[PDB]
Image: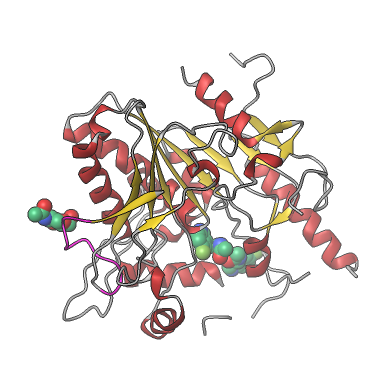
Amino acid sequence: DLRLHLLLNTSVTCNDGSPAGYYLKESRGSRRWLLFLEGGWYCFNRENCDSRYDTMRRLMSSRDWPRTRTGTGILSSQPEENPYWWNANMVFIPYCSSDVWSGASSKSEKNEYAFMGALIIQEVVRELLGRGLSGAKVLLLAGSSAGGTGVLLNVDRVAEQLEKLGYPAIQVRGLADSGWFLDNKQYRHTDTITAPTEAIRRGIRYWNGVVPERCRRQFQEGEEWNCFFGYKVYPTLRSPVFVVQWLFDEAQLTVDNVHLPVQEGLRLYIQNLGRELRHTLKDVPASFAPACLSHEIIIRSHWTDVQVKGTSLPRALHCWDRSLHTPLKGCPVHLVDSCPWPHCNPSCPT
Ligand SMILES: CC(=O)NCCc1c[nH]c2ccc(F)cc12
Ligand SMILES: CC(=O)NCCc1c[nH]c2ccc(F)cc12
Ligand SMILES: *[C@@H]1O[C@H](CO)[C@@H](O)[C@H](O)[C@H]1NC(C)=O
């Protein structure tokens, strides 16, 4: 089990001003550290955040968090469940800032909520350095869904923080799961429920959201929403990043207004979505993109079962490690399906 630690700097807070925190399991015979960012949508105005506080409060507050959590999937310490990194030091960082891990604003006389996702990551890293992270050789920043986009927004900031603090030997890398979205034309179009790009644009202003500096300089003021889309922010990053994304991701289809007898118009829409996603990954050398309709993530216990071209995700991640010690015989790292319909890969989740 991973044990809860609330942040010693209690000014770094969840939405309601309670302290943020992290869950930790140490592995004293290991110099590898895995820091995982939880997901769970976001909120972008007072009324929408007030609703989230009533029925999704664990994503806005630490008041009700449990003392322990069990590590699963890539966070498991059992080699049978986690062939990749079972002996690593494991860290799970709860998502309680509702800002896609981008915020840097405190609760004040003008702000009903605090949005501190970017500062939470920095404070966790700072406090772990006194608990053994100072001895690491690799820090893998991973995350799923909103946490996967959070990896893209924050991995280079962690690298810069460790360099400025005096630890240039720690190699910082990223693993972004299910956070690589397209700002595409929707299948049907039209408050909250009526487009993601406009909700993110309003969110950034509400949260005082921050994006990586090279991407910010490309798109400039007012246009920072572009950096929340993987295919636009990825080329600006310097740390190595491995991208995991279903070709027919369920969250992508939901915001495209698709809810699964499929007739011709919808058939062509779904096929075009898969081809566009595959196209965005052509110049991403470390990636895993199966032709499945799914919302499942890499902290699930059966994450080892899916394969692309006969290679599982734990294997591809192992080959990525070897590559960062020119392709490797029988040890591939770029794995993108080419078949054009959900479940054309027989290994897709049931
Ligand atoms: C599903 C969707 O709306 N995707 C387009 C907006 C977007 C970009 N990165 C995200 C991370 C989490 C999230 F909830 C949304 C986003
Ligand atoms: C997932 C998501 O937010 N897609 C919508 C992006 C969008 C906003 N305005 C548009 C106008 C034309 C177009 F092709 C796309 C757009
Ligand atoms: C706590 O964190 C905030 C936000 O990063 C920082 O400004 C402040 O200096 C920190 N306090 C201490 C005592 O380290």
Does 87 sit above or below residue 111? above
Q: Residue at x 40, y 58 (%)?
A: 224
Q: Residue at x 81, y 44 (%)?
A: 345
State the image coordinates of residue 282 (x, y, percent, origin top left).
65, 36
Magenta highlight range: 7-16
Which quadrant of the structure image shows residue 185? bottom right
Does 291 sit above or below residue 107? above
Question: Would you say the magenta stretch is mainly helix, strand or loop?
Answer: loop
Residue 133 within the segment the image draws in magenta: no
Query: Who is closer to the viewer here, 301 or 232?
Result: 301
State the image coordinates of residue 311 (x, y, percent, origin top left).
71, 30
Q: Is residue 56 left or right of residue 259?
A: left
State the image coordinates of residue 137 (x, y, percent, origin top left).
34, 25
If the picture is divided into quarters, which one holds ligand 2? bottom right
Residue 14 within the segment the image draws in magenta: yes
Q: Is residue 192 left or right of residue 312?
A: left
Does 323 sit above or below residue 18? above
Query: Who is closer to the viewer here, 81 or 285?
Result: 81
